[PDB]
Image (cartoon, rainbow, N blue to C red; front, side):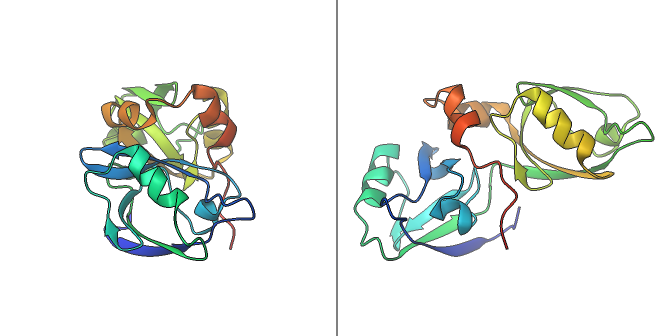
Length: 191
């Protein structure tokens, strides 16, 4: 979570797509979906990022529809965005024990208990938080079985990016749970 603002320069693909869905939250505009293999993935936009500006227009107070309209009508060559890095999210570093455990229970990607005397406990992992990413890989929409597989196959240092559930449930409202699994970029970034 790069406590800071940054400029991205996007370029619409063959089909005039950038691969992004935006959502209005508390009079800001936030990244609800990044489509795999899109312009938005390659320049490195992440779920929960805030869009402060689009081509130097301020996004404050915009509807989701207006944000989408503005993107749909840009001189597609070059869209500049101003991004605040995942402002609703925090990152927690934990170490698996001898038995490969970090020490919580989750359900539908949401943490529901902290196991006594674990790395999760010692690092103050919270319940009622949705898992957004593991070691920088977006996991939103994946089955619980697959978030488990990612944790098991991770090395012994585990980084998880979490969000309060209330804020999570507000951002994903009005997107069917099939589209989250289907189309949310779950890939390791390319260099």
